[PDB]
Length: 122
Image (cartoon, rainbow, N blue to C red; front, side, top):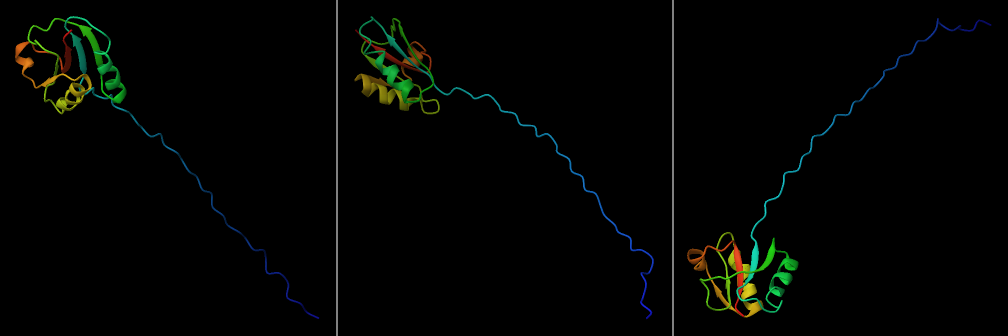
């Protein structure tokens, strides 16, 4: 007999999604060198003097430069430091490496040496 017929027609809906990326600005700033050591041999002798610089730079110190220079302020094998930041630490170690008289910023007034110096007499 009589059967119910389809009403009209059913509709449908939907949505659409979008996205966007954005660039990130990242910059790095240059580093600042701390404290340098420099081995001065006053008379010129064996490289055992420069050996203090070698082990030191390999220990993780900034610059270790070796040259022959007449220090008129020293009269004995002397490892000099200044007390800026902690420069006393490196020369306190090297003074024992070389086996020399370790001294404060006293040669600083006498001659004015750069940073920390290791003076060896020969």
